[PDB]
């Protein structure tokens, strides 16, 4: 049915609901076998990963590095200051050299087009470790965390309040494929990419889900089962701090926000979190799934790597989505 | 009897003589099995370590990284420039995320209070990789090196000449627990922390050992079995170079220093060494145990990790202390 | 016959034709067993490597790191910004500490004399990862790539056009030992080291091969089976960009260069490549072996490490040289 071996993972728009559910099934299987049963599964023995990071990272870095190694493989952390990329060398040449020396690449970049060049020029899987446009592997952790909390995903309403950034784009490329509704509030002038919105409208129509884009936080939060935010100033945007602090006033998630949400509301944030987007009462609430979510970055990137590099079949019963 | 699994190791003041002897016993066992018998002991297979370094390191870095990996685990080297800590993220949040992704953390920091926050907020063992206040794992290497040289430790006199810094504080938190005497000379105004001195007086009283603090190098060296020094300008103190070079004149360890020491005198230095604290004749003397000492940083951090993360029992006969 | 265990590899002038052929035989054996047969060969299990890099690297870094780990060992990446070297610590002391903590060192340096100090002061193998004077492990990859292309090496003419740098010096220390001829063109004032040239004349005489040094690109290319170039501005020489761009005009390798070469001509470049030394038509030609060559950096550094640290014997039939 689902065949993911050898594929790239640059964005969730290139994946069906069934393929993304397969990745969450494998995540749950690997988490059960290793975290709960204590098995050692050397599924990536004799394999290596090239990790290119052009931006800082705590969770993507740790989850990917300890995750690849936990399956018996060798992760190699490469930064801008150590390798030749950009300066003495082109991306086409870097891509061909990585192909012959590693079995896959995870790259945290600025330009999504750099991930496209890497996928075209390399003959090994390229995984997006976050770009300015999309962050697909974050949403894998998010939807596994919500399936574990609610015991299913179909019919949940996701309520985004914040910037029209990479995280919202990845939710837009995937929520309807799971039968989930999306209500998203951004400041005026900080909307999601018109092309992404257009494709999210199509997915909503195909799956019979709702998509609401607004500038009002309480309209996005109304009836939502999950409240979701992120920093107002993403990496590479620090020059705009002053303008963004002014434009985003009134967009902090608080218990006033939650009062309008469904009674079973929970909260997500990809982290790192700052005091601006959400207050401490919601961030550290018993309803906040932020640290479960962060943990699931590890079991989901392990599943991505196993599905793109092996023919391993999940032993676990498929979770209810 | 001794149970160390799950504990943090932030300072040796939180450890009894019997617990620290257990760590040196395990070090000796692991050194004998792997270095001498050539066994491969995958005791930390399926485990990972988060290594946070806010300061430079050659020995703590190499001993910890090659040591964790030699036992089958995966070490992950994280610096200030790569992870979000300090800048985009709090230590509480970093601590909770590390907990769900690694099995332990070793952190070389400035503030000991940062290690306290990490231990309180993480549910996994936190090991001090050096702070401004204490460096417990250095003293583990030091006392293993002296037990190997002398075939026991009880009744030795340690003679510190130098700054009232982290290394002297760690010796003060541990020497009396082994029945060792301490005679320490620092410049006036560069004494050890009054709280540490107070607690070292109490340990000396409980164990019936002597504690002498002086400003005279030859008084500290008199009758000492081990001469010990370190840099006059510790990491983070480079602004004070001029004032310290002036204040520490006359505190260089030389053969004049050694003439006053016991006939079986040896020499220790945690490294890196500069020409100021000790001359070449003592540093490279046959009595200098500096490079044995540096090697034992590896077998002792391996023992720390095995004792805090497993239920492994030493097969070796307990060494005489 | 050949015994390489415990030796350093600082330059190919310290190696006979038979010893270098042994290293290419082991490379071919390891490539066949692991890449083609898919075997997992944990030959360096329980071993570690200290990797000191004072300059940037993509290929030496990846090939060495994934290569050491593919054989079951642990590679440790150490940079100038993380370890004490240069600043708080001497190379003699760093060398002795590395000896007791790792099983070998690979170091990419500026001064070849730093590699000499490391080899004298350490009791473990020191491998040159590139210095200003020599880059021996590059030529191992190059000659394996040419043996795979041509099915033998004896009698080939290597045609260097470019700077009288580390790569040309390493070709000069080795081509005649394989019965290969060398014709090399550099700009006036940018010749190879007079001592290296002198020793290359002696090797040419002992092996009955030709050695031609010229300032004319087409004289170096005439009748050559392999065209070889590299950057005009090596790492550490960026201050000389203006003077070198002017002095090296007319030294770009093009199809005009190739028109003069033997009919079976191929092309090599150690990478990273810039547009100055060679054009796109030659670089991306079907005759360009640049990306095969880059891959073989991995199988040859694996063979170096296995031959200096173990008693493993190649199972493969010896390749024809
Ligand atoms: N919009 C934010 C998203 C950060 C995602 N965070 C993570 O993936 C967690 P990490 O940075 O610790 O790996 C930005 O682009 O800056
Ligand atoms: N008082 C000194 C102690 C240095 C300890 N050295 C070590 O642990 C050896 P390393 O720095 O190579 O890891 C200071 O605080 O600067
Ligand atoms: N003459 C050049 C040689 C570069 C060698 N390149 C390599 O070894 C490939 P890498 O730098 O990606 O490891 C110089 O000294 O700059």
Image (cartoon, coloured by chain):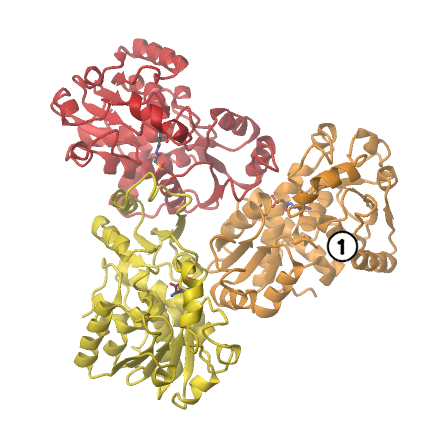
Chain colours: A red, B yellow, C orange
Q: Position of residue B265 (x, y in %)?
A: 41, 85
Horizontal and vertical percent for residue C111?
65, 58
Q: Which chain carries label 1?
A: C
User: Which picture quadrant has residue A10?
Assistant: top left
* Residue C164 vertical position relative to residue A315 in the rendered view, above or below: below
What residue is shown at x 28% (from left), y 34% (from top)? A274
Find numbered disc 1 in the image and state the secondary structure of the residue it sits on: loop
The answer to whether B87 appears left or right of C250 in the picture is left
- Viewer-closest of A131 and C289: A131
Residue B189 is at least partly visible in this image: yes
Labels in figure, total: 1
Q: Is residue B233 left or right of residue C175?
A: left
Crowding at mark 1 (Cα within 10 Å: few <14, some 14-19, many 20+): many
Residue C6 shows in the view: no
Instruction: State the residue at coordinates (73%, 43%).
Output: C146
Q: Within 8 Å of ligand 3, the CB of disc 1?
A: no
Residue lying at 46% horizontally and 79% vertically, measured from the top left: B288
User: Foreground: A227 or B237?
Assistant: B237
| Foreground of the two, A66 or C308 | A66
Indicate the quadrant containing the N terminus of chain B: top left, top right, bottom left or bottom right: bottom left
| Quarter of the render that holds ligand 2 | bottom left
Q: Quadrant of residue A300?
A: top left
| Residue C114: percent from left, percent from top | 62, 61
| Residue at the spot of label 1 | C174
In the picture, measured across the screen, residue A25 lies left or right of residue C95, that is left
* Residue C291 percent location from the top left of the image: 65, 37
Q: On the rendered image, what quadrant is the C terminus of chain B found in?
A: bottom left
Q: Which of the 4 quarters of the picture holds residue A172?
A: top left
């Amino acid at each position: 049915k689902v065949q993911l071996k050898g594929r790239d993972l640059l964005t969730l728009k290139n994946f069906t609901g069934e393929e993304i559910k397969y990745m969450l099934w494998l995540s749950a299987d690997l988490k059960f076998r290793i975290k709960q049963k204590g098995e050692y599964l050397p599924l990536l023995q004799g394999k290596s990963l090239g990790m290119i990071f052009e931006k800082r990272s705590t969770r993507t870095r740790l989850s990917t590095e300890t995750g690849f190694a936990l399956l018996g493989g060798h992760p190699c952390f490469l930064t801008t200051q150590d390798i030749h990329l950009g300066v003495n060398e082109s991306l086409t040449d870097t891509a061909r050299v990585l192909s012959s020396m590693a079995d896959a690449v995870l790259a945290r970049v600025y330009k999504q087009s750099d991930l496209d060049t890497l996928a075209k020029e390399a003959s090994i899987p390229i995984i997006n470790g976050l770009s300015d446009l999309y962050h697909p592997i974050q949403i894998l952790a998010d939807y596994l965390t919500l399936q574990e909390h609610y015991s299913s995903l179909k019919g949940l309403t996701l309520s985004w309040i914040g910037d029209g950034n990479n995280i919202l784009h990845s939710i837009m490329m995937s929520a309807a494929k799971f039968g989930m509704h999306l209500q998203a509030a951004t400041p005026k002038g900080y909307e999601p990419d018109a092309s992404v919105t257009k494709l999210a409208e199509q997915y909503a129509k195909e799956n019979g889900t709702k998509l609401l884009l607004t500038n009002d936080p309480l309209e996005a939060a109304h009836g939502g089962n999950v409240l979701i935010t992120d920093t107002w100033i993403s990496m590479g945007r620090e020059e705009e701090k002053k303008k963004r602090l002014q434009a985003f006033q009134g967009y902090q998630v608080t218990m006033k926000t939650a009062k309008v949400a469904a009674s079973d509301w929970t909260f997500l944030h990809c982290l790192p979190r700052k005091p601006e987007e959400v207050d401490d009462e919601v961030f550290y609430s018993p309803r906040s799934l932020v640290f479960p979510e962060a943990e699931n970055r590890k079991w989901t990137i392990m599943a991505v790597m196993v599905s793109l590099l092996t023919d391993y079949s999940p032993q676990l019963q498929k979770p209810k989505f």
